[PDB]
Each structure stands twice: as structure tokens, then as C-alpha cells.
Image: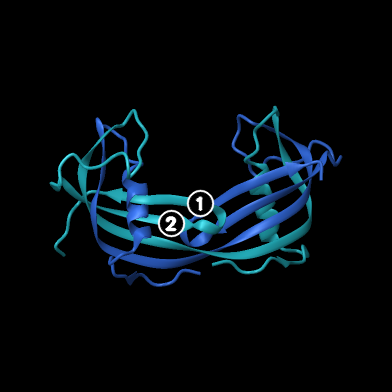
Chain colours: A blue, B cyan
Amino acid sequence: LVGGWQKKPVDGNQLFTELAHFAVGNQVGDREFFDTVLEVIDAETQVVAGTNYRLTFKIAESTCRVTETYTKELCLPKTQDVKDTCTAVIYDVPWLNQRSVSSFTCGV
Amino acid sequence: LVGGWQKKPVDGNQLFTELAHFAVGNQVGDREFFDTVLEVIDAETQVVAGTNYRLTFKIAESTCRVTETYTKELCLPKTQDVKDTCTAVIYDVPWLNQRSVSSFTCGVNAA
């Protein structure tokens, strides 16, 4: 789900300052020096919920070379021989079209 | 905020197949060919809510070179003189120790 944007007070919110520093400390580009925060002046927040998935599954070697772009429909199993069993943890946030794998381990 | 882990049936659930394929198709290590998914056998889920932060702030040029490490406490402003105003959106998910900047732009507003 995604919630509405809400204006918040800047006030004594340390986290705002911490998150601003986090953003501006990560802008390199074509600057000789980093810029840094003098002050925050507006602040809005928005709940954004995703789902974290822990999936266990059987794998096989596929026919696709890793140079290629993977697809379910192109990268079919060479043989119906199980190779391993694996567990993966995937965080999915459709609202921001983000999806990430945090862990992936086999020999389960 | 984080919901509880819940066991879910594999059943037909096409999302789980899509998510397994997604994970396996992003593993290129120690392998000439991608592995692919034969079948899913367990599934658990956890709602995790993060917070998206839209922050507007005034910046100054700092004393730290880009070669160096940024820290608020080391990279103090040269002068208490504004040089630009910027807006950033940051998605924070402390529960997964993920944090990301989705946009960073330096236009200023008396909107």
C-alpha cells in the first residue's frame, strides 16, 4: 500500500537532518567538494508498505548463458534433473517499482 | 513498522514463481549458464512498511573533498552562507537497513 504525503514540522527532528545529510553526502557528480546541510526547511512523509518474501525452491541448470538477459520463458531447464534447493529473501515494493534480493543460499 | 511472518501455501501462487525466477535470474556467480526454477516448496511473507521522506533544505559548500568520506561532523559548511536549495526524496526501511534516494534536485521554491 501507499499512504498520502503529509507535511511534518521540522522542529527538533534529528532524523530529518540525518536523512538530508545522507542525501547530500551522496552527491558527487562534478563537484570538487561535497555540499552539506545548513538547514532543512520543509519535510513531508509517506507510508509505503511492501512485502518481504522468503521462498524455497528447486533449481535446475538453464540453457541460457549468463551473458544473456534471463527470462522464465527463454531460460528453460536443460534437463528435469534437480541440481539444488535454494532459499531466497525478496523485498517487493510495487508502489515504487522496486524489488530486491537480500539473501540467496542453496544446499538447503 | 513490520508485520509478522506468515506461512503461505505455494498452491498455484504465480507471484511466488515470478519472485523465485526473479531471484535466480539475478545470480550470475560461478556459472556459465543461469539456473532456473523448477518448483517452489515453501513460502513465508512479512509486510514491511517503510517511510518515504520528501525533504527541502538549504545547502552550503562543505570543507570535504569528494575524494574523502562524507560525515556531518567532519564536513561542516565553509561559511554559514547559503549556496543553493535542494529537494530530496528518501525511502527509509530501518527494518531491512535499506535506505535510498529516489530523487535529488536543486531548484528552490517560495511556492
Query: Is A62 displayed left or right of A51 in the figure?
Result: right
Residue kind at label 1, given as amino acid type = Gln
How far across and how far down the image is residue B104, in percent? 31, 49
Task: Determine the image quadrant of residue A24.
Answer: top left
Q: Is residue B5 above or below residue A38?
A: below
Badge 2 and badge 1 both on one subunit: yes
Q: Chain letter for mark 1, please.
A: B
How far across and how far down the image is residue A58, in percent? 80, 47
* Foreground of the two, B8 or A40: A40
Task: Determine the image quadrant of residue A8.
Answer: bottom left
Q: Which residue is mark 1?
A: B98
Farthest residue in the front direction? B73
The answer to whether marks 2 and 1 mark residues whose Cβ atoms lie closer than 8 Å is yes
How far is mark 2 from mark 1, CA to CA? 8 Å
Q: Residues within 10 Å of mark 1 (few under 14, many from 20)?
A: few
Q: Residues within 10 Å of mark 2 (few under 14, many from 20)?
A: many
Q: Secondary structure at mark 1?
A: strand
Q: Which residue is mark 2?
A: B91
Q: Chain letter for mark 2, please.
A: B
Residue kind at label 2, given as amino acid type = Tyr
Query: Is B68 displayed left or right of A49 in the figure?
Result: left
* Foreground of the two, A16 or B3: A16
Q: For the point 36% across and 70% down, which residue is it?
A: A5
How far across and how far down the image is residue B102, in percent? 39, 51
Question: Is residue A12 visible in this depiction of the protein?
Answer: yes
Question: Is residue A73 visible in this depiction of the protein?
Answer: no
Q: Secondary structure at mark 2?
A: strand
